[PDB]
Amino acid sequence: APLTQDRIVVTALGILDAEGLDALSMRRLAQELKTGHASLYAHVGNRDELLDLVFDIVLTEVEVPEPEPGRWAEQVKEMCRSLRRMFLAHRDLARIAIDRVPLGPNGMVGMERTMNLLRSGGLHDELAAYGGDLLSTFVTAEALEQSSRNGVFADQLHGYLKSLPATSFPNLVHLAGPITSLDSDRRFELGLEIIIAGLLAGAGE
Amino acid sequence: AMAPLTQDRIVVTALGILDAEGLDALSMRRLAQELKTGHASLYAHVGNRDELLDLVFDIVLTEVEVPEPEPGRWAEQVKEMCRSLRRMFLAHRDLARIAIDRVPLGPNGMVGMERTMNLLRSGGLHDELAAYGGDLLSTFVTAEALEQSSRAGVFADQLHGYLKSLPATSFPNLVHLAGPITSLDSDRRFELGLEIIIAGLLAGAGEAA
């Protein structure tokens, strides 16, 4: 097999999947591929450059539906859920993403389709452009937080808040559970609805 | 001259280093040098570098003003409180970097959170929406800040020029939206995202009721 960018990225993604981001060093990479450092660099560049490629390669997993009449909110949700699923299937991938702009080949194609869908809901240019950005940021941040629970810290945070003097901190005592605790699924759906409802509001008539 | 060290004098000095020189310049050694004290008395007062940063984070939160609820002005008061948080980050180099992984539950943080939740609930938000909304608002403000600081006028005109000169037959939306996707000034992005989240919160409180 000739060394290629795509072979390097497949191998890199496999290490990441089975061992996590910290295990993906260029030294480890070169060693797995049975190649030298110079070849590695020539094909993918430095570590951050390689991670840009590994991010783009997994974006094929995100499906943006073709717009349908009267289904805009559900379809935008379906797209955000597809992005969530991508992160949940690749450990530490949200760590790579939380940082980056999805402008590689698959990212471009996906952004074109995303913007098609968003504009189709009647969103003005700035709203469609910024709303795609906000939704992507939201999804990535939530996936990162879920991955961060994969304990008791959140539980000690609960006891602390619950035992505050209720006369001085009535809201923190009362909301002690929701503030510390929320299920990943429920917070994702809540945040997704909030952003979608607010985009619709901005769209107006 | 030299007064016994207090926690406050130490933190204020640390924040000064951060403001002028950034987070990497702020080591315990630099801090002890700047205070002209020994490392025992520094550590007795503020612990390790991570504990110090928890303290620097809480001290600047004094700057965030969360208003007492005013009936009929809910949406603009939430904006106001969010703009105050943004102001604070913009004032303090590298501060969103410290904030991003931290829960603001020191003194200033906990009071700020109480007042925030007071304001959110005063708008008729049910418990989960109030609690989650507070989080989503702080998360959004902090992310924006991290990135107003992570920006440059070159890179955007490159990305703009890539998008703008894409085959219009292939990428009609990317070509047409090259400006917004690439341009958006910070103020504009900030206000749009604020509008969006506040409308969605009211929308959620309104179905509720």
Image (cartoon, coloured by chain):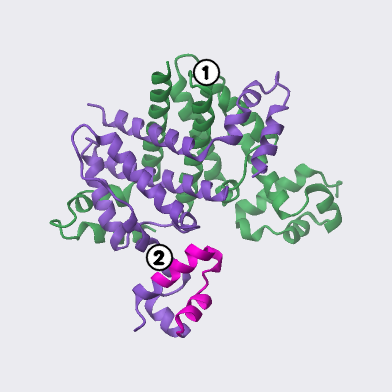
Chain colours: A purple, B green
| Image quadrant assignment for residue B119 | top right
Q: In which quarter of the image is the N terminus of chain A?
A: bottom left
| Image quadrant assignment for residue A42 | bottom left
Where's residue B158, x and y in %?
30, 62
| Relative depth, front residue between A74 and A122 | A74
Number of other residues with Cα within 10 Å of mark 2, as a class: few under 14, some 14 to 19, many 20 or more:
many
Q: Is residue A26 magenta?
A: yes
Question: In terms of secondary structure, where does tag 2 sit?
Answer: helix
Question: Would residue A189 be found to the left or right of residue A166 on screen?
Answer: left
Kind of residue sitting beneath label 1: Ser
Kind of residue sitting beneath label 2: Val
Give the foreground label among 2 and 1.
2
Magenta range is: A10-35
Where's residue A158, x and y in %?
67, 33
Q: Can residue A48 be seen in this view?
A: no
Q: Can residue A76 be seen in this view?
A: yes
Mainly helix, strand or loop, the magenta region?
Answer: helix
Both marks 2 and 1 on one chain: no
Look at mark 2 in the image and give the residue it sits on: A54
Q: Does residue A170 sit above or below A35 in this rendering?
A: above
Look at mark 1 in the image and give the residue it sits on: B122
Which residue: 16% across, 60% down?
B167
